[PDB]
Image: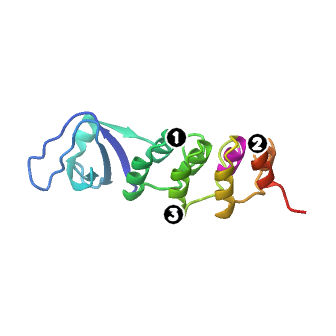
Amino acid sequence: GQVKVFRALYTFEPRTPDELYIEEGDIIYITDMSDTNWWKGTSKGRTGLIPSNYVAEQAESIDNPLHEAAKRGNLSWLRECLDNRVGVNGLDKAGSTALYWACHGGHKDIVEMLFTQPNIELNQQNKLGDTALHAAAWKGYADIVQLLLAKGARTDLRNIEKKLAFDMATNAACASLLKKKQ
């Protein structure tokens, strides 16, 4: 089963010892949804049981928690998402990955962190045909471009306007990193 993420809107006090305690605003990671009434989840490092009904009514489904953490420069939450086995290669409504957003925003920590994850897809293209590397070049982040290249990002992929990551760069250091040696 795939992990689903929520935010607690209200507080839940456990009635048994196997039940999970959750405060308003806390983030909940649901790992097992097989039972009708009782879900298994993690919240603030602890693992317990939580009624599907509390989740449906007093909590809030977050569709792309990893993407969201990346966009906002939230290293901690991203780290928490990854520790709770949220998929690194999940695509948002625009076809972008968490890596795409972290590069798009120039967050070196978040980028380097996603790099330590198994199976991280560097070359995913979104609906507009952009890779993470297109975005880092466009936005002029030379260090992110370097890091993408070092990790082996593809430089041959073309977006919907037929433009390479190179054709996106206007910053001189990015342009230089992405042109072919002679």
Q: Residue at the spot x=40%, y=55% of the render?
A: 2
Q: Residue at x 8, y 51 (%)?
A: 16
| Residue 53 shown left or right of residue 69 in the figure | left
The kind of residue tagged 1 is: Lys
Question: For numbered disc 3, what is the local secondary structure?
Answer: loop
Residue furthest to the right = 182
Q: Callout 1 environment at 10 Å: few (<14), some (14 to 19), or many (20+)? A: many
Where does the image place residue 101, in percent across and percent down from the top left?
57, 44
Q: Is residue 136 magenta?
A: yes
Q: Which residues are magenta?
A: 129-138
Which quadrant holds residue 163? top right
Q: At 59% from the left edge and 59% from the top edge, which residue is drawn?
A: 121
Q: Nearer the viewer, mark 3 or mark 2?
A: 2
Of 134 and 169, the residue lying toward us: 169
Q: Position of residue 32 (x, y in %)?
A: 30, 56
Residue that mark 1 sits on: 71
Q: Quadrant of residue 112?
A: bottom right
Q: Which residue is mark 3?
A: 116
From the top left corner, tell me how far across and down residue 36 is, in percent. Answer: 24, 49
Q: Name the residue type under label 3.
A: Thr
Amino acid type, mark 2: Asn
What distance separates the C-alpha of mark 2 from that of mark 1? Answer: 22 Å
Question: Which residue bears the numbered disc 2?
Answer: 171
